[PDB]
Length: 129
DNA sequence: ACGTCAACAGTAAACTA
DNA sequence: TAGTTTACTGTTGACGT
Ligand SMILES: [Zn+2]
Image 1 (tube, rainbow, N blue to C red):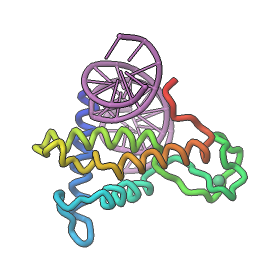
Image 2 (image 1 turned 60 degrees about the vertical axis):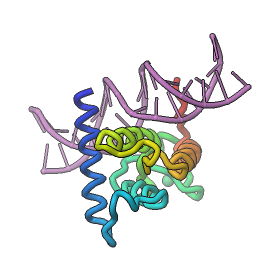
Image 3 (image 1 turned 135 degrees about the vertical axis):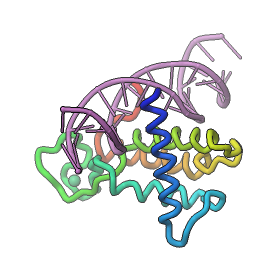
């Protein structure tokens, strides 16, 4: 809880610095669905999860026995949880719930695409056991 | 109204400094 | 070492039948 809230607060300030370091400078009210997805793609550089391409032999193998030049991405579970924290952080800082940019349909569709593509590429299942 | 899903909450690990 | 945060887990509330 306390670690979760500080994690949420840090993500909210990280998203704030992201908007200020955006070029052109991006305001919160102008954070369209495309811009939120642009933010989620920007975070792939900090991911640690190997997502194999369809030409790599290790596609669908969660524990390859050799390195490959396939890119590292944010896992679906990281993005799913981050969206939950940012959804709350937006409303905890006075944002109207029905204007929540992290609740836009484009966010839901993107997370589903990441879930289905990574499950095939990684060979893992994101369903709750 | 169970059966699932959505909407966040919460924990674990290992990498960075 | 200790802090961070990606990655994985958990669950109340809401949805769907
Ligand atoms: Zn690969």
